[PDB]
Every structure is written in C-alpha cells, then in structure tokens.
Image (spheres, rainbow, N blue to C red):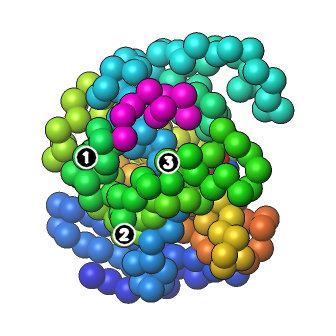
Amino acid sequence: VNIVDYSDCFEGISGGAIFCNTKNKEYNIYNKELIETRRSPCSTFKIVSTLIGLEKGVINSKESVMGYDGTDYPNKNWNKNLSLEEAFKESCVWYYKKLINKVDAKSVQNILDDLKYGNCDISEWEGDLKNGKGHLNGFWLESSLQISPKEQVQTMAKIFEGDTNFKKEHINILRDIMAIDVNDANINVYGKTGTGFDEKNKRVDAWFVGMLEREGDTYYFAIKSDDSNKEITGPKVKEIAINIIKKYYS
Ligand SMILES: *C(=O)N1C[C@H](NOS(=O)(=O)O)CC[C@H]1C(N)=O
C-alpha cells in the first residue's frame, strides 16, 4: 500500500485517487481519507445497473432497447429509442430508470449485498425528490446509496476478474461499452463518469471509475473530487484521471 502524490495532475482541484493491481496487490493511494469516504455513486452506478438488467433479462445485448415513449428531453440523444450502448455513453437517465424499475427491490438488495456495494442502502428507491426532478431521480443519485472510492475499486475488480456470478457474456458487454479512447494504443482504458452535488456538505461528487490494462497488468481505479466548485464534473475528473494514467501508468 503506497501513498502517492498525484496533486500535480489534479491542478488544484480537491480530490483523491486509488489504483489497485490485484496480481501483485499494489495499492496506490492519493488522499487516503477521501478514498475511504462513502459518497453517492451517481452515474457510475450504471456499471452495476447494466449488469443487473442483463442478469434479470430486462436487456440482453449492447443493442437492447427500453421502448422510448416520445417524452421531450433537452439532450437531443435522449429523444430516441436508443440502444444500451448509446444510453450508457449518453448517461440517458430515463433508460436506466425504466430499466431498474422493472427489477424488484429484493433482487437489487441481494446483488448489492453480494457485490459489497458500499452501504447497500436502497431505502430511498425513488431518490432525492426534494430536488424537484421527479422521476429523473433514484437511490443511486445523491440519495441513500453511498460507496467509497476504495469500495468502487474493490467492486470493479470482483466483477472484471470474474469473481462474481454475473455471466461472462454480460461482463464482456459492459467491457465493450465502457471502453474509452485515450489516444494511446498501448493502454486499454475503461470507465464511467458520475456527477452529483452534495447539498448537505455543499461539495460536488465527481467520479471517474474503471480499469486500465497495460501489458498483462490490470489496474482498477477510482478518481474522485469533492471540491466545493460546482464547475467540477465527472468529465473534468476523467480528464484528471487520464493525465494520471498517462503520467504514472504508461
Ligand atoms: C449521473 O451522474 N448523472 C447522469 C448524467 N451523466 O453524468 S456524467 O456526465 O457525469 O456521466 C448527468 C448528471 C448526473 C445526473 N444529474 O443525473
């Protein structure tokens, strides 16, 4: 377990990082206190909810659709019968809300418990209704479910090392749709951003969680900001993560 200084890459933004290679159990940690602190996963939960939907047969493949009903949304790309692959990359809220609401709460509870997914607290199934966004809410978006960056890495590793009961075919669908292009063909990067604002503490929850493969070695990682600046988003934290990968993991 190595404590490291990645502050140079964070360019003044408050956050932490954890990279884990489970082959040689090398844990690299920047800001250990933050890395151990549970927060809402926000849209990073789509990694797990995709697998839930696949396992329960709500969806079947990266082409699978959820039956768009014509509702008007400001994001162009949400206004169509988009596939799993597109809904994942566009973080289409209605697609993933419809998906999870076809699954009974006990099945979700048991999968989160099996994955050790943070506090596994789905008690506020409907999410943070006080923000006014109604059905564009859920337990995973600044609501009851909370997970630490370290626990995210532990979950990612369990899934992608094949230590869960999720089907290999379903894991590979997730892998496909999480693949990122980082303009470096000598590393494969996979991940998902998340963005939320913690109203209680007046800080962002900005995430980039995923994995990294470079010549036989795989690193599971989670980068997380808790800055008080609302301009700090998951996309911004993904930039930071990419800088760290290019600097230290090439
Ligand atoms: C998830 O974090 N969300 C869904 C969507 N995607 O965010 S991302 O660009 O960080 O991946 C918009 C923000 C957020 C939400 N408010 O639902």
Q: Is residue 75 left or right of residue 90?
A: right
Q: Residue at x 44, y 86 (%)?
A: 33
Name above or below for residue 218 compared with residue 60.
below
On residue 110, which mark appears?
Answer: 1
For the N terminus, the image quarter is bottom left
Q: Which residue is mark 3?
A: 125
- Near mark 1 (Cα within 10 A), the count class, few <14, some 14-19 or many ≥20, is few
Q: Residue at x 58, y 13 (%)?
A: 67
Nearest-to-viewer mark from 1 and 3:
3
The answer to which of 80 and 212 lies nearer the viewer is 80
Q: Give me the C-alpha separation between circle 2 and circle 3.
A: 24 Å
Q: Earlier in the sequence, mark 1 or mark 3?
A: 1
The answer to which of 238 and 232 lies nearer the viewer is 232
Q: Earlier in the sequence, mark 2 or mark 3?
A: 3
For the C terminus, the image quarter is bottom left
- Residue 203, image quadrant: bottom right
Amino acid type, callout 1: Asn
Amino acid type, callout 2: Lys
Ligand 1 within 8 angstroms of badge 3 C-beta: no
Q: Is residue 165 left or right of residue 38?
A: left
The x and y percentages for residue 29 are: 39, 78
